[PDB]
Amino acid sequence: QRHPLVHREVADAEGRRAFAAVFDGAEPFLMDHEQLFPAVAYLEMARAAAEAADLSIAGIRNALWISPLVIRDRACELRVVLSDAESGRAYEVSSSRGVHARGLLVFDEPPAQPARPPALDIEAVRTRCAIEVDARTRNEAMGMPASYDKLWIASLVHSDHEALASLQAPSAPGDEAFLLDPNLGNSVLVPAIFLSLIQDGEREWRFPYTLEALWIYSDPRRGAYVHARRAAEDGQAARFGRYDVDLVDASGNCLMAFRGLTAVPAA
Picture (tube, rainbow, N blue to C red):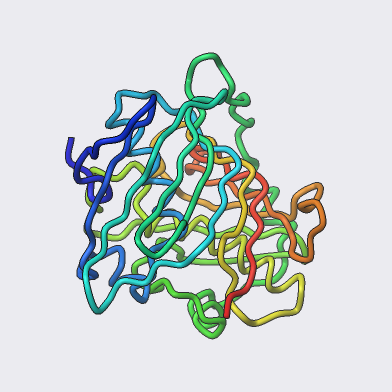
């Protein structure tokens, strides 16, 4: 099955399966993101690799992002290794430049996915988010790697601890091979990161560091709103805040739920 992020299966041992892809930097997902492999793309790669291995994935738990991968001058191979774990499979994404991401792929069996949240009362959320912003200007000023025009964000409102973004799809569909296209994934994350910044009074962009979970309920391409919101608790010994963010359709149904995301600055 063709996928932009998983090109071939590679040999491994002991109840491990490994997959690889080579990127040259001319891929739209990279070109659209300052040549930096998006955090969200690792999640898609891991899921796609598991799908290639005939596994059925309900979600991802305990995701971590380590070293950034920048691909511009020369092509590079990225490898993802899957190993047996209680949840399903552990994954590690690496290259000759180190480890970039890791986490846990949660299988559909035995059931481990939390019940889909109830439909979001979008109007209620709109009434409690008083501040309207020019998302393009604000986020670009903060150093977001993503090209705003390639994102789905059309509007953004917020309170001191909650945000709601409306979405409009790009006219040209994505590569339909993607379950979560990076542009759409970044659209979901941007409102949460924006919230992290304005809660801390900061202006430097933050990148995903840890994520407690990602649950996939239905096709994210039906997205209409992104609802982000400081989590009930932050990470353990944590300087940086933790956020929950959901992608919902026009009826408020949850398409994807990101639980416990912590984003942090970079050098």
